[PDB]
Length: 110
Length: 110
Image 1 (cartoon, each protein chain N blue to C red):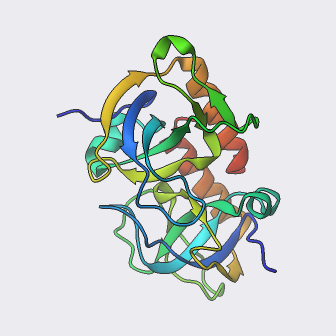
Image 2: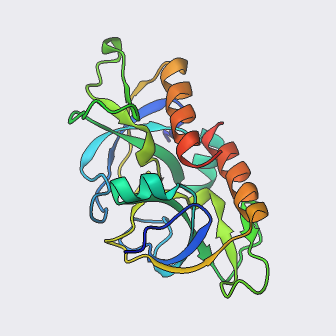
């Protein structure tokens, strides 16, 4: 009965995807709250990749979480987290969630 | 040489998708700016349906844009717009963009 909540890092399959969208099973930083995620079966989450290109939209995860890679803030997507088999991994610190949101917000024109 | 820009309504294939994610070929409201869209080949956009479910995160498109329906603000996702074959259709008015952004921002925890 796990419902991802905002700030959770979950393992999720980003496949299926198209083109340059992130694919593959990897952590994902959940941005939407569990109340939405649980009522819809969807969530907004950003994939984490170990193939960091060092660009500013990549938000690094503190080593303490045990989740390698960077959050690709700009790659946030509406995801069916049951279909994509979300599995809880960890919880990101508030500052990572704030940085990802600020960067994604700038991308979305907020 | 079209690069989608923020506020554009484009026709796009939301397939491939998983599960409850919005699929199908339909309009999309682009939120991210062309500078990003053109450098990455990705964009953040929300799907449009001409058949509203009647929920608050739908944002109705005004008449006379030649694209009708509602923008599903909560279904925004990072999309490879070349893979999904974005075709420019129209430009949404600033108030639609702002309402979509405000709704999506609430979803994303901003």
